[PDB]
Image (cartoon, rainbow, N blue to C red; front, side, top):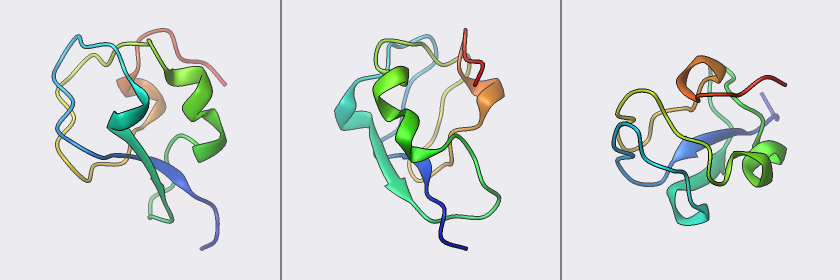
Length: 66
C-alpha cells in the first residue's frame, strides 16, 4: 500500500471543527480520505465522534465531496 490517508491524531468529538493538530497521515487499509486533503478539511465538522487512530472516511465529514 503506499497511499496515505488522514488518520485521527486524537479523539475528535462529534460536531467539532477539524484543526491541523487533529489529523495525521498514515498508510492504512482500507484507504480513507487522501492525506493531500488535510488542507481542505480544516474547519469542516465531523458528524460522529472519531476515536484516536481511526481513518477518516468521506462519509464522516459534513460537506465533504472530492
